[PDB]
Length: 217
Image (cartoon, rainbow, N blue to C red; front, side, top):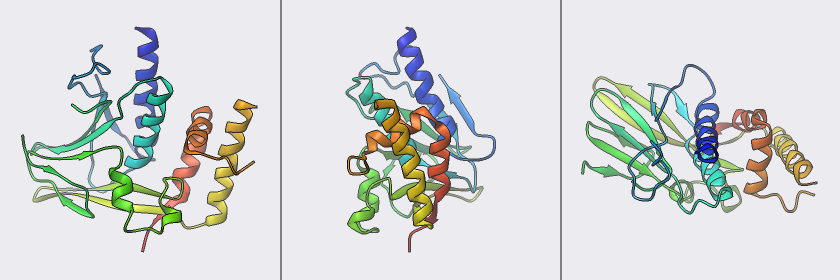
């Protein structure tokens, strides 16, 4: 299982590289049944940390892109759950009880409750908050700021955009040019081209996340 192992390696390392942007990230991986239909094996588990921001939409869509490139039919699922000792993010490569909560600006997350995030949940969250031209991940991205205290756990979902439109556009140019060089104009630039370019140089992904820094009003 080397082709499988390489893909699983890459998927885990997308999370490691892009879920945050600073500090020690506590990412645990673990069975030959991560891809198997009907399995409840997550790819990895991440302990969330008070005050940190997690780039859920970007990582989600990056994982979805790699899976479709490998002809894998399922789309990932993120599960945030609080067991009373800690809040974790579990990244499943497919859909795998306690109250299951939906996305909103402030999701109180008591013990034994979960939040499930899937393919269209980020667009549904953004849809009423941003104008149509800003709806795509390239312009507006959903993040999660963790609020974890002894007396309350709360997942705070925010939409971030670039404050500097010119610098954001310059990063897009670099990514587009990287995609064009791998395949050998701006009018065709797609989410696939975006992740193809970032796949070739992760630093371009870091550049994008760095510019997507301002919560919407």
